[PDB]
Every structure is written in C-alpha cells, then in structure tokens.
Image 1 (cartoon, rainbow, N blue to C red):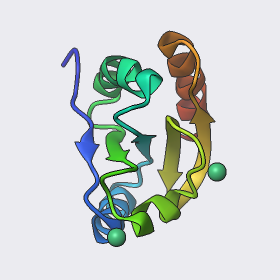
Image 2 (tube, rainbow, N blue to C red):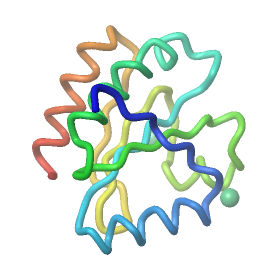
Image 3 (cartoon, rainbow, N blue to C red):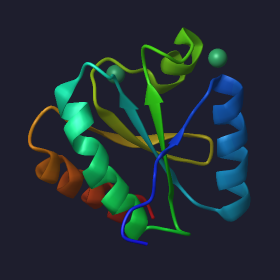
Image 4 (tube, rainbow, N blue to C red):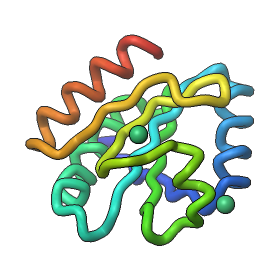
Amino acid sequence: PTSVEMEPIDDSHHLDKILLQARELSQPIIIDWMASWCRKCIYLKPKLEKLAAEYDTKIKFYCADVNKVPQALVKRGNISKMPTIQLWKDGEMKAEVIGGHKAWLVIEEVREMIQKFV
Ligand SMILES: [Cl-]
Ligand SMILES: [K+]
C-alpha cells in the first residue's frame, strides 16, 4: 500500500483492546492525538497515512480527536498539545513527538522515534 488510514480510537476500553492486540504481536503502535480545528493536525494526516503504509503489518497507526473522544481517553495519553504523536508498546507510552511545525519535518522526527523502538 501507498497509504493506510489511521484507525480512530473510540474510548479507553478500545485503547485497552488495541494494546492487548499489540502485545500479542509484540509490536508497538502509533497514536496521533489531534483536534479538527488544529490546522497542523489536519495537514499532517496524509503524511502520517503515507508513513503508516511504510509500516504496514509492522506497526498499526491510530488517531484520536481530543474533542470528540471521552475525556478519560485523552487522560490516558496525558495530552497537553496537538498534534501529539505517541509510540506505545507493552501497554504504555514509550515516547512522543509534538508537532506544531512543517508536517514533513514532524514525520522525520516520528520516523526516528519509530526506529528507536521497533
Ligand atoms: Cl473512556
Ligand atoms: K503532556
């Protein structure tokens, strides 16, 4: 694939199931914590979906709209800024990247993070 759609996270129970599945596969996941009014979040989406395709079958990518999902789910990420791109593994956040600058450059920093933990 050239692009893979990020899967939305519905709530904290969904995150729990996502992390159980990642554990079964011994894989990390990526979560894009974003907001629909956040212009950089919107511009990052296609670039994240291109990066997700590069990791198809190796790292699943997810997204969560911090205004739409329950507050309890946002608290699981300890989010304070958007977009926040987190790598989780073994049931917890291992590292994150804060966007808020050109999408390509955020992606390269996310790629470095993935290289560290994959
Ligand atoms: Cl929840
Ligand atoms: K934070």
